Length: 333
Length: 58
Image (cartoon, rainbow over all chains, first blue to last red; front, side):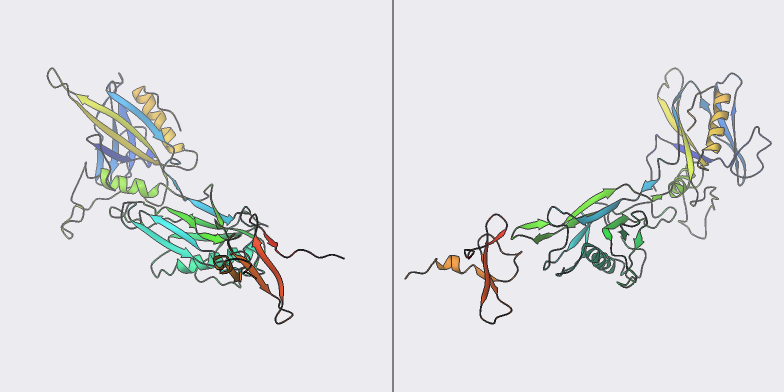
């Protein structure tokens, strides 16, 4: 990624809270250190290459400080519930083609001027029920999608038998009408799909979409046959891949800005965050003001990360330490 | 012995889907049992199809 800065921000991973210096044995350790008067604050971190200290924090020049619970950076995958509007007809008309158009915006490019469309077509018959329609439409969608020899499709297409209403039965281009057997399928689902992520080159990004039904002739009039309802998501992209590219970036203000540019000729940088875990976060914003004529402020940030076991034990213990040391009052998430 | 209606309104006498005919079209239905009969003639009244031929009773 590439983020914006209040002229600088630096990141320090906190895998273990220690009580004092000389207890920093393993890399990624952290201990907050402050004067007894509570004038300044700084963090002594155990880098892979040794021990290191954060910049100093004049506790009367600190602007804001707040911690994030690691549930605020998870991206919920958008999922639609496509159905038939009983307004038009609770069942398929016997001779019309039910096309469904998936409108994808900010496809490969960044702009919404970058649009991609994928169709799922179906024709109905005299005896076609709503379930038979849903499964044939899901199959058509998955087969027009998921022709990828590349990866998981732009969206994940599921179905739901009214007997469950909770389990989502997948539908892939390899799925066959024979393995979908239930007779009470009551909707077609389409869930946003997590895209690839490689450290420092491909930031966490998604392709939003909209199911755009087309018009069928019901009673001589042209009418839209579907209802693209947005259901509460059930699956999220965890924080691990944002903190990873964040450290990748904030470890170039403290270290090497060249990252692979002369490939053999490199300053290898050992990062301490695994993109497979989840991390709470704590930002502290503060400035440095000079003397008589140098009153201009130099604002800076010091952000820390700590894994979330679901109860926020690590960061909350870290919060308590910083508050007992600096006398501050940061809220324990 | 004039035409019952003009041609612009006879042109719109069609054969096929009951769902696809507009308010401007008359629908014919060829009887499937007999080979040259008609079973109903319909046109849209209020979005619904209704028989033009008067119903007979005894």
